[PDB]
Image (cartoon, rainbow, N blue to C red; front, side, top):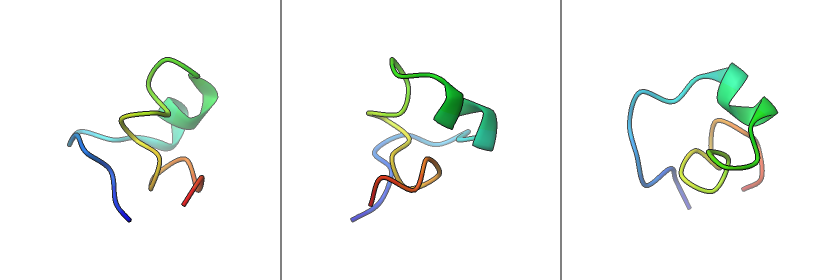
Length: 29
């Protein structure tokens, strides 16, 4: 699994409307 978008940031893990795109940077998967 990986993020489906680029420009991911660890601050994007604080967003639940961007963690879907950046799940790898969120640590969801």
